[PDB]
Amino acid sequence: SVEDDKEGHLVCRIGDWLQERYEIVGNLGEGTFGKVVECLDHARGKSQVALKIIRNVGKYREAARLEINVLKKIKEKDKENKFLCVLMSDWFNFHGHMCIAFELLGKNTFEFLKENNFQPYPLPHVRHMAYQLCHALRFLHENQLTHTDLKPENILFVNSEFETLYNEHKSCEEKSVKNTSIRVADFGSATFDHEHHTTIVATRHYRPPEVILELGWAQPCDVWSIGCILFEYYRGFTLFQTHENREHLVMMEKILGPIPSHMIHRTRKQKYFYKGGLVWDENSSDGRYVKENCKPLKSYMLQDSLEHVQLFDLMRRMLEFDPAQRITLAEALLHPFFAGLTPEERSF
Ligand SMILES: CCOC(=O)c1c(/C(C#N)=C\N)c2ccc(Cl)c(Cl)c2n1C
Ligand SMILES: [Cl-]
Ligand SMILES: [Cl-]
């Protein structure tokens, strides 16, 4: 009656039920953890929900039990539900598969970008999403918590319905999201201040230099991740398209400038350095890639106007090498870039 595939995924499709309560009506996404399906909750007047069904594998089941505990603590802190985090409705162990029911939201910010053929979000959409990311993460940080896995894939629109607009300048159609309200998802890696901090955190492209250099990490990890995200929303391509540490550090250098000598002198990861400088093969396939494609951050500006200059100033401050020098989210919310927000956007 209950079937799992070779990888421990629960074999389930549209028309299937869980706990004689949740009825699967569609597929919303997939990750390494398993699957996310749309359900009608038959115990809640057929309420539409998103059900995250986790793989029947020990590592994933434990990571989901950790996420559940985090969502419960967040629920205790944000009673009013005004701090822009996914809202856990229920949770259960279903034959070895952990399942987390959430209030149904729209597409994640990466999927909307992918479906808009990587055509970037306009600056006003980027501004409101930044303001909300800064606000949402400032709350969790104030509660002694660090997300660690912020990435476009983990940010969801409350509603992803869009308007198809013909971009005159590109001679093609563009999908413009009608409502830029977002929510932060995936607390499977979220760590409290007093808990054990793994040496390595974050998805590579969104990994800060202090994690690469094994200098320990805290709340500033998330600020770096946001800077990476805002760039990706602005240009539509990842800032650090890398699969390797040495190449990662070279990119950071080309785009942002020299790695502070204080971080070099402190790191135990000396293989990346020779004579106090980053060491790399300029003639390898990575060396050539970086030298051709990785330019100073400023060069990626699409327009010269005041609002574009401020996005780049905020992003640069989000991408400060030294976590101690990195802008805090409390300071970010004060940046002149957010003066361009509409009163509806500012007020929440
Ligand atoms: C792309 C991997 O994950 C997801 O599909 C996903 C995820 C998760 C997780 N974790 C992450 N992006 C969702 C979290 C909450 C809600 Cl309400 C929904 Cl709809 C979610 N979806 C559809
Ligand atoms: Cl520790
Ligand atoms: Cl990787």
Image (cartoon, rainbow, N blue to C red):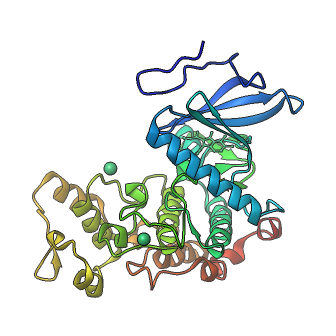
Q: Relative to residue 342, is residue 275 drawn left or right?
A: left
Q: Relative to residue 68, is residue 214 drawn left or right?
A: left
Q: Give the quarter the ligand 2 occupies.
A: bottom left
Q: Position of residue 29 (x, y in %)?
A: 57, 34
Picture residue at 63% right of the left edge, 76% below the top: 337
Q: Relative to residue 296, is residue 224 drawn left or right?
A: right
Picture residue at 29% right of the left edge, 62% below the top: 248
Quadrant into which the C terminus falls? bottom right
130 or 200, which lies in front?
200
Q: Position of residue 60 (x, y in %)?
A: 48, 41
Quadrant into which the N terminus falls? top right
84 or 348, which lies in front?
84
Picture residue at 67% right of the left edge, 46% below the top: 176
Which residue is the extreme one toward the top?
A: 1
Which residue is the extreme one toward the right?
A: 45
Vertical position of residue 330 compared to residue 23: above or below: below
Query: Hey, which quadrant is residue 324 in on the image?
Result: bottom left
Picture residue at 62% right of the left edge, 18% below the top: 13
Query: Hey, which quadrant is residue 131 in on the image?
Result: bottom right
Q: Position of residue 158 (x, y in %)?
A: 73, 48
Vertical position of residue 132 compared to residue 275: above or below: above
Q: Relative to residue 89, is residue 303 drawn left or right?
A: left
Does the image show residue 169? no
Instruction: Tally the numbered discs.
Output: 0
Vertical position of residue 172 compared to residue 226: above or below: above
Q: Position of residue 228 (x, y in %)?
A: 46, 63
Vertical position of residue 27 compared to residue 198: above or below: above
183 or 227, which lies in front?
183
Does the image show residue 48? yes
